[PDB]
Every structure is written in structure tokens, then in C-alpha cells.
Image 1 (cartoon, rainbow, N blue to C red):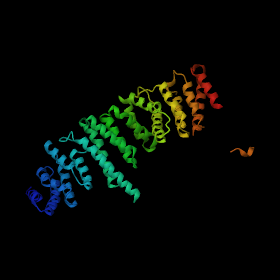
Image 2 (cartoon, one colour):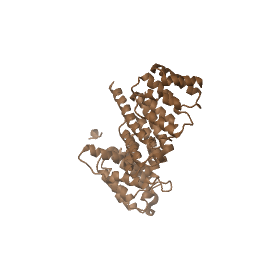
Image 3 (cartoon, one colour):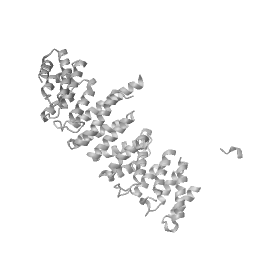
Image 4 (tube, rainbow, N blue to C red):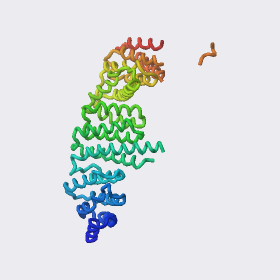
Length: 407
């Protein structure tokens, strides 16, 4: 357009205040002529984004650049130049614009041609930045609705999820290692549940559309097993993600890891450790109880009874009410859920001995959790004897157990 011709001249050559106004008008012009070439407009304006400029000029330029990247038929070399312009040194206050620019440049993560190999390291960088800035806002909120920093962080998580979905092949193994670490950090220290929901979805994405490297698995399982247990409002979300992982090549490794939380365990004099590992143990129980209802056909890995029980013994010593209650709740889901296949061909004394250990955790005037699970198990073990009888292999182990627990 001859009008657009003018504006660009002023955008390139005007005194700064003229450039700002041109920027604003072009932003309107571009909107009204999307098919028109934004390339020279880009170059005219890109310097105005520099952090040395005042707000009004960076801002009006960002808005113009944002409209420009939308242009459909950019070349790849042109997309590359936009990415480096929009992603590099920029004012802390402008992150929202960068986010949106990148989002629009990529079409919500779909197209990263021109910066195939730069995209993921950039996202990982921005995660650190974005999270850091949300946490601070939230600290100074507690000190002195969602903050702009909260909103920025959500939108970035959404972007990271989408880039994984559409373009995980351009993620190298080592950037993913980086990305995973960053998400788990945020998982274990964030005041906002939505960040956790968001990080779970990022991990879901990884597993759904790419892969978690073997050496990260323990940590994903740690973190997810913990959220699963400790953050009840996200239990379904975490289980979904854990299920995917379980039904995958990691299945075997995941079971092994989950048991390790039990088998690895060792009662530590340092209560920061004792709890660090207990944290892990309670989650493993939660996830195991859920896993153990699954079948090879459903695609889920089986668990060794011997190992499981080996793991369960260690744990039953420590702890009190709620943990003993969990140990039991697991065992109760094994005997009723029909008996679980894992224990049909098997000696039940070992398990019954653990069960009992959880029973260690509990004048006519003077008469004034775990207990809930025992009444559940007794009833079930009682029923198994009654309904099977001689056909039930393990009946004598059943019987010895009930004698322990009555008394």
C-alpha cells in the first residue's frame, strides 16, 4: 500500500516519537493487510524492542512485531530472524510480549521451522525465568486472583506442552534431561496447585509424544508418586500420567523403582532423611496399591509378590497410624479387588506377618484408622476361609493369622 509505504518510511526514518506512532498505525495496517509482506516492516521496527528504549516504544513495537510474525508465507530464513529478534535480550517487563510472539510465530507450538534446534533450550531457559518471577511475586504477595507472572507461567507451560506434542523430534536427549529437571524442581516447590497440574501435563506430554530418558525415571516417579499421594486434588491427573509410564517400556523399571522406595528404605537418625525417604515410601504404596489392581492384558507390569512383601516388611517397622493404615490398605486391596492374582499360588504367612505388625500400631466408672483396616482384613480373610475352605490352599496360614489378631 502507498499509505503503508509512508508509514514504513516514518517507521525507519522518523524521530523516535514518530516511529512510535508509525508503529501503531502499521500495526493497524498489517492487521488490515495480512497477505502483505511484513519483512521490511520487521526490520524497520526491531530496534525499538531494545531494552534501552522507553516502555511506550518497546511496547508499540512488540505489538507490531506480534502482528508481523502471524504472516503465513514467511520463508524459513525469515522465521529464523524473527525468532532471534523476539527471543534475545529483552526487558524483564516485556516477557509477556516475547511469550506471545513466540506462541504466534510457532502457531501455538506447531511450527518451529527456522529454529528447530533452538526452540527447546529456549523454553527451558524461559521456564526458569518464568517460574522465578512467579515465586517472587507470590512471596511479596504473602509479605505485602493470579498475578501477571502466574499468568505468564501458565501460558508458557501450555506452550511447552504444545511444542512437545508437535515437535518433540527436534528435542535432543540432553535438553529433555534439562527440561525434566526444571519441571520437577517446580513440582517440589510451588505454592500453586495449577503449576503442579501444569507440570504433570508437561510430563504427560513427554511420555505421550516423546520419551523420558532412563536416568530421569526415578525422579519423575518420585515426584509423581508424591503428588499422587500428597496432593489429593491432583490424584487422578497424576495417576493418568503414571499409568502411561507404567504401560510403557519403563513399566518394568517403574515397578523396580517403586519397590526400591520400599527395599532401599533404611530408618535414618537424620529426620530430614527419614522423612525424605518416608515421603517416597508413602507414595510408592499409593501407586502400588493402584498398580496392583492391574493386569498384563490391560498392559500393566506385574509386581513380584516376594519383593513386594520384602519391601513391605522394612516399612511396617517405622511410622504410625496413617502409614500402618496404608500398608494395610494395600494388603486389603490384594485380598479383595476377587483375590488378587499375585497371591493365588503363594504362601500367605509372610504377608500375614506384615499385616500383624501393622496391628502393633493399633471400676464400671473408669471405662472410657489402623483399627478400620484390620476389621476389614479380618472380615475378608474370615470370608475366604468360609467360602473356599479345603479348596483354599493357604487356609492354615489364614487361620494362624486370625489367632494372632483376635488376641
